Image (cartoon, rainbow over all chains, first blue to last red; front, side, top):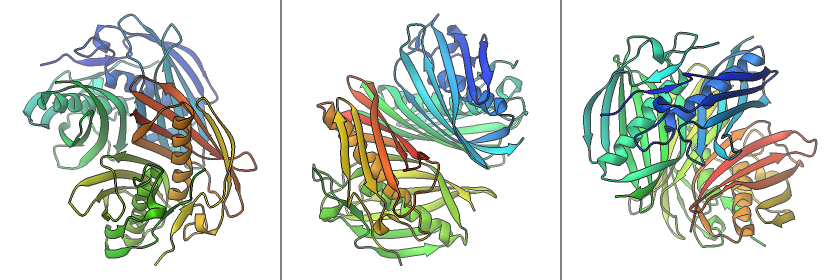
Length: 121
Length: 121
Length: 119
Length: 119
């Protein structure tokens, strides 16, 4: 048995402009796994959502085809995670978004890359 | 502005034995994105959690180094998603888990691969 | 200093039909890295080429957007590697190919997934 | 039928120091796929080899567990490709290498991430 995993119970959108997005959020109990670390799925969801925001900031609509993520450092309760998303390639039919998460001490938590199919403007 | 994304508000563990895990869950409103599809992060979290369960079913403890996921078909409200995880490679220090999600009609929703570092027994 | 890495100096196409591909090849010296193992790029290239063959076998043309690979066991000189490719998802606009490599002892060497844009 | 795919028939190592690597190479005929573009496996092998070089430059030895690559723009015959590698995370047990390839016009060709187990 285990508890539900939730993401974006709180957040602040600091920047969302022209393929560049910055969002902060506070790690809470629903963010965690059984070992008291930020859940792998929670962290991925932070990245994915900010990828979607990048797509919107480009004035586009899109759907994710593929995503890859590297976990570097555990996130902990009360951490303020800064999620920065950037469109690193804007193609005709596809976009590639890089998203990285750093904690309040500037240490890299995780990084992810999203391969998006643009469905509209 | 957007709503929180949640995963495992409900579930049933059908099978969890020797590196093979099957878990069902019902897609609900907190599962969805703004377009009314199962959120990319939600689906990833379903897969990741079942990967962790595979690790446990092997009698091991581990941490995810890297994960990749392919989105094939949208999940929808009230879908019953069947999440099946399998350890496809059990190494000395690393494990590779394949996890796939199918809906109640047997259609493939998504598939993911997790590269785990075994930290204990 | 290091030597060039080559792939497909030899191969045998056992099957190439309707999204299902099997190709065999023998690991040679040009296949190897400094440690005498099959080079990661060599193994990846085997997989990618067979992905392209799956694409051809479906009567389609496509361009690879993204690829992921997991290395499981080292390949060695004189290994006979069996490369099997399958289209695990055939969409209207995208295809997903799974490719796996096993050696002559049936041991899993590596596996990869290719995300293709149908052109 | 298809020809062998080769990588590093030529190269110049511009920098290999403390986790930072730059290597250049000229795309040749053995680099190409049937469509006359740089082969996906060729590009990947360029990236992987430079990842291995980052590893060496850190004074470490390692084995690649997993790799991901995104293809952004086709490489062409006679392109001069600049391959840049960096260790973006150096852990005790694992390293993560980012590798990117740009052509002579400064256009991004591809980028890849390597997940290495330090041995």
